[PDB]
Image 1 (cartoon, rainbow, N blue to C red):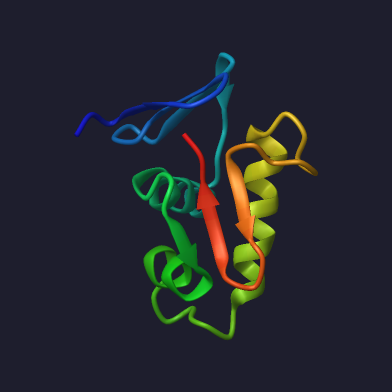
Image 2 (cartoon, rainbow, N blue to C red):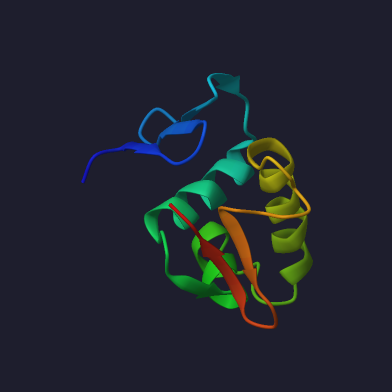
Length: 101
């Protein structure tokens, strides 16, 4: 299963909770990391906003859909070449999100 995930200039050790780009250490927030993980562990699958709020928080569903948008933004800001044009952290409009690689 291998807890060492690599996608662009980013390498993420899921076990240690550490991330390098590309590479020196990018520092994530504990919340931003549980979301990265969930996303990394569902690579390529399209996940609903409720699915994501469930897996990151649990009773923070669903009346807290905005936190998910705010933390996707943070993830893009830190990990994406162009936060405005994500290549890995992809939105499925009206549904949820999809992570590539």
